[PDB]
Amino acid sequence: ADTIVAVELDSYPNTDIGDPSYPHIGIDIKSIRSKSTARWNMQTGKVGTAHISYNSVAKRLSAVVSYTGSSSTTVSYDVDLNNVLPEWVRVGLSATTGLYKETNTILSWSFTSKLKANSLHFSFNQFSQNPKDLILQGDATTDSDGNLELTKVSSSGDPQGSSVGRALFYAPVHIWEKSAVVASFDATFTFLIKSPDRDPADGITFFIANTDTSIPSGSGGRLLGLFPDA
Amino acid sequence: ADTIVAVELDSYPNTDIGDPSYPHIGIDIKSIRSKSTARWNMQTGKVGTAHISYNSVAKRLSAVVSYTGSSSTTVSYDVDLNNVLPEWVRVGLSATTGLYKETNTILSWSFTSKLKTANSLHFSFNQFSQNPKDLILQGDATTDSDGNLELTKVSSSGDPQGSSVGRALFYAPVHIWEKSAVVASFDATFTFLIKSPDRDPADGITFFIANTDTSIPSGSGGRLLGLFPDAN
Ligand SMILES: [Ca+2]
Ligand SMILES: [Ca+2]
Ligand SMILES: [Ca+2]
Ligand SMILES: [Mn+2]
Ligand SMILES: [Mn+2]
Ligand SMILES: [Mn+2]
Ligand SMILES: [Mn+2]
Ligand SMILES: [Mn+2]
Ligand SMILES: [Mn+2]
Ligand SMILES: [Mn+2]
Image (cartoon, rainbow over all chains, first blue to last red; front, side, top):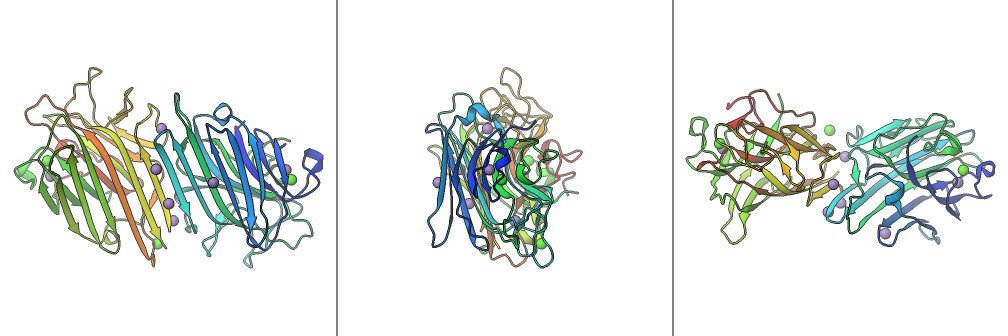
């Protein structure tokens, strides 16, 4: 079973598995049952931005999601990630649609990791047709507009249900080493969630996992393509 | 047949294949016979620093090698790398030894690529782990307990060995160009320590850019720096 650390943008309330009764963003530490969550005032059809950051001294994983012209949503959790994650990891984005759907379009994504100092940084303001520097899993694809469509969309751009997909950066990341003075990382991605459904689903996540991580079987829908069970 | 673009720190003069008659640094475009070279006043036993840069507007690949408290060595060559390299590549470092030898120790390596279609990739190693999962080690290349990358074999006692070849490629491919892109550039730097028991150290170290699936060619040892199958 993979080891997962993620920040979820949960658009669909799955109260039968721990979610609060409303769209929310949360911090998941080895389980879909977020250790911390904050109400997320979604704005489908509007481009949002998510920023995630962490450093080994403060030991506080934080995330902020926002849209232009509106107050943001933030969430944090005190945790020693070096204790949870292996020294080497791959970082990525995931998304899923189930009975209900939504577009899980990524317009841009950047990540920076520093180990005190060695470093890894990448930035995509648009994605290439054949992103050789990305590992596409499931239905994840990049469209003609240079955007990353984590889940299946029609020619018109209309979302489809029962879809799952993720994109991991090709190169493993060394997030920690013995005696390391300080290790830190931060990620940012812009997204566009659209949907005809009264209640869109299921969400998008930025996650960090073991380097050989793959879509767990039965991880569709509410499990955001990250966990095998609830 | 890989496509190679490299900046060579040629410590051994092989005049039989076009090398000038003195240690030198050079810019190689699909051939070991440098398109441009400059005399390299080596400081064996001293830590050196090499800097390589290029951008699609200026179209001038330049490299500078220096040591603390000494005059630097520079070499340049005008060339549109878009007419040579494929759109996706892997970057790396190579080194070899032949009858004569030398340590080809890399103490640090950084690289930055920018593509304004601006997308970018950047990595830096101030030390290397024993199990560098973000590096593709080829040939004899290995990282040591000191955290340094030994491109070519060195005895457990630190003494270099001849007839060795090794390379280290960064794991993720690099997108250096795309049609209609506005501008693209890359920057690379690495520090190295070349030590030798031989009056004439050989054969050299290089920073190269090649097709993503690049591998050490057969017969690329010694004077071929682990980059080419022949000296054509
Ligand atoms: Ca949910
Ligand atoms: Ca030579
Ligand atoms: Ca192209
Ligand atoms: Mn949730
Ligand atoms: Mn930040
Ligand atoms: Mn850096
Ligand atoms: Mn690209
Ligand atoms: Mn030469
Ligand atoms: Mn950048
Ligand atoms: Mn490392």
